[PDB]
Length: 201
Image 1 (cartoon, one colour):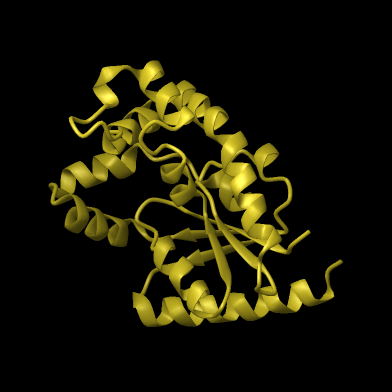
Image 2: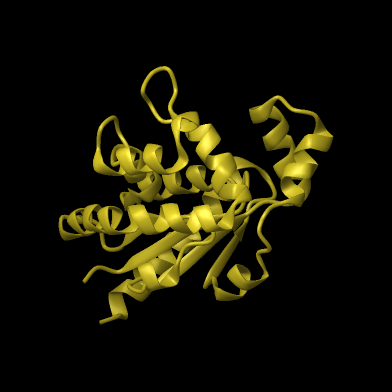
């Protein structure tokens, strides 16, 4: 229906910044993560199933979901990552399709998770994977998490291997030198996607 580019990134890759640069070029960006939060708002069906599944530990005093805790669980327990992805996939897909129907840009960017199920995103024309070198990731993680460098390395040490996702990706944006070059790279990708969407039916 619409020429769609999947946006993925490893840890502390700079990918939300990449999304913003695409946004600022007039491209419609669909944020699957934002949709997931929406559809796990207080007393939504998925919110209820999540709390019943994981139990009271993932409910803050707020009655809001403990999203930090859930991320920790999802990252360390693959069976739970898959369970949660299976739960949310049907509702998230319906929201994505709504936004695609009203897409006003020449192509669309869909921000999706690093280890996204392809069977759930078979309609993507392209996949873009944003990565940052180890040093850059640590700096980003220490500043965001306020943690020790050795804890950041330990966090990076446990990330999923990218070999398979690097192979599959049509384009890999190495974010290795500041915001200005990042913007320049996004610009060239933008022109590439415009070109390919123009000649693709």
